RNA sequence: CGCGA
DNA sequence: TTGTCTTCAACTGCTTTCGCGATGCATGCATGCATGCATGC
C-alpha cells in the first residue's frame, strides 16, 4: 500500500504542504505581508536543496514541526 | 404426503 | 427303521390416474486488548 524507501518525496510534500498551510493562516489571519511567502520559499528552498545535495537511501533527515516554526521565525527575522 | 376431477 | 402327506409357520410381493413441492466434531479465521517490533526524525 504505502510507498517504500523513497517516500522521502511524500514526506517532503506533506511537510512543504503543511508549511504553506500555516502561511495561508498567518498572512490571512495574522495580517502578515505577501512577501513573507517568497522569503519562506527561499529559506526552505535553500535547505531542501541542501538535503537534496545530501540525498541518499542512507538517509539522515530530521524535518520536525520545530523546523517549520524555525523557518517562519528565520524568515520573519530577516524581514 | 401436502394441492386439482 | 423308514417312508411322506401331514401339519403348523418363517419369508415376501403388491396398493386408481396426473400436475405444485444428514449428524457430529475438529480446524481455523474472527474479534479484541496488550505487549513488541519496525519506521522515522
Image: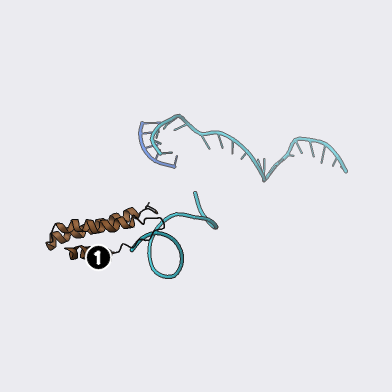
Chain colours: A brown, B blue, C cyan
Identify the chain of the residue marked 1, using the numbered disc in the image. Answer: A
Residue in the foreground of this view, choosing between A42 and A21: A42
Identify the residue at horizontal 27%, vertical 64% (top origin): A67
- Residue A37 visible to an observer of this rendering: yes
Q: Residues within 10 Å of mark 1 (few under 14, many from 20)?
A: few
Give the answer, above or below, for where A4 lies relative to B1.
Answer: below
Q: Secondary structure at mark 1?
A: helix
Identify the residue at horizontal 19%, vertical 58% (top origin): A39
Identify the residue at horizontal 28%, vertical 56% (top origin): A14
Point out residue A7 in the picture as x, y percentages from the top left corner.
Answer: 35, 54
For this view, does A37 lie left or right of residue A11? left
Identify the residue at horizontal 20%, vertical 62% (top origin): A75
Tell how many labels: 1
| Image quadrant containing the C terminus of chain A | bottom left
Point out residue A36 in the picture as x, y percentages from the top left corner.
Answer: 17, 59
Point out residue B1 in the picture as x, y percentages from the top left corner.
Answer: 44, 42
Residue in the foreground of this view, choosing between C31 and C6: C31
For this view, does A9 lie left or right of residue A20? right
- Residue A15 visible to an observer of this rendering: no
For this view, does A1 lie left or right of residue A29? right
Point out residue C34 in the picture as x, y percentages from the top left corner.
Answer: 41, 70
- Outermost residue to the left: A31
Q: Which residue is mark 1?
A: A70
Amino acid at each position: 500500500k504505502l510507498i517504500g524507501h523513497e517516500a522521502k518525496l511524500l514526506f517532503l510534500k506533506s511537510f512543504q504542504f503543511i508549511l504553506k498551510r500555516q502561511i495561508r493562516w498567518l498572512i490571512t489571519e495574522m495580517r502578515f505581508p505577501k512577501e513573507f511567502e517568497h522569503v519562506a520559499k527561499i529559506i526552505w528552498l535553500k535547505i531542501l536543496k541542501t538535503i537534496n545535495d545530501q540525498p541518499q537511501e542512507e538517509l539522515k533527515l530530521q524535518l520536525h514541526m520545530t523546523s517549520t516554526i524555525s523557518i517562519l521565525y528565520l524568515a520573519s527575522t530577516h524581514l
